[PDB]
Image (cartoon, rainbow, N blue to C red; front, side, top):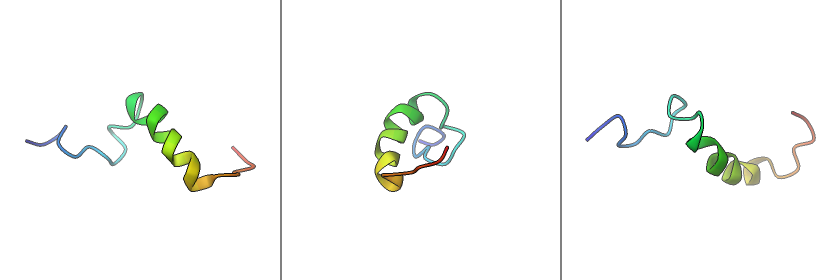
Length: 35
């Protein structure tokens, strides 16, 4: 029970931990007038 069990760090981030990730991560930056 590991590797996939608790994968929030960066190597799991790439395609599925981006769309739903950046979705909640947009509230952490809210305005964000940059890149």
